[PDB]
Image (tube, rainbow over all chains, first blue to last red; front, side, top):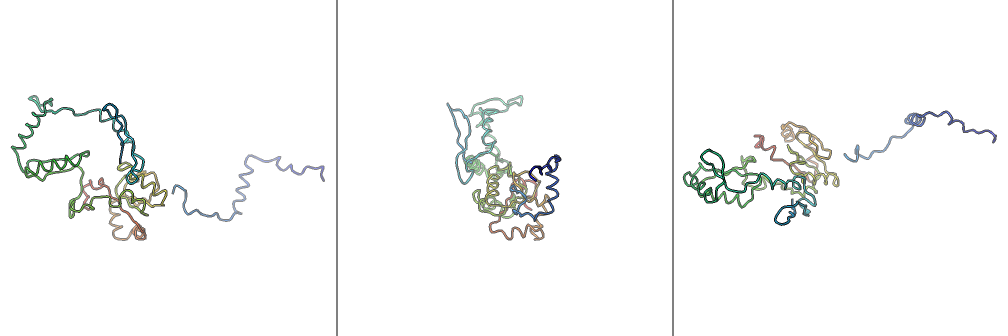
Length: 42
Length: 230
């Protein structure tokens, strides 16, 4: 129960874990809104 | 653009901007600011005439003026002529006009070319910036034909940039894809596109159709290329 630590899962995280997870989540997102122009300089 | 010349003991020190909200606001171009240095170099200070060897030598005002008046009296009519430079004032221009008019001459020419076919210079608005530099702030679309206003008229381009930034003014260029410090719609390079816009085929005709305050600007550089009339 309390004796065991249940947050060992981060002990095997690579330098690319966050970016890989973002790529995995990329297909769960709603389409982003548009400002009307491609850049403030346009 | 209005400037202030700062002198000291009868010598030019620097050029500063002066505020005119309608012409240059508060800025001047680098040429305007830093080309006063040439006023102290390569200057003509004394009258000169050709001597027997064919070289130019100094002489007094009376000698040079008499030698010019001799040929001005000897010839007449179309044999006399005049050319105006790029830094000439109205007083000298009208003086030369009257002087050659007293000799029955109309050959008063300028280096810059403006097509004289039709109206020519009879109607003033045929060769002016009728929208005025301030009025650029009220336009909503502008068409530029064969100009690079960034270098031909830096303050005009600065005003266009300001209107682009603040009024969402839309710019299109017909000419070489120059850098104008803002994004513009490059319609193309060949002059025939103008006729296409005249025909109504090119969609920019529809763009100018829907504008409340359209604007077309044409530079004299594109009028130099012998197609000025067309």
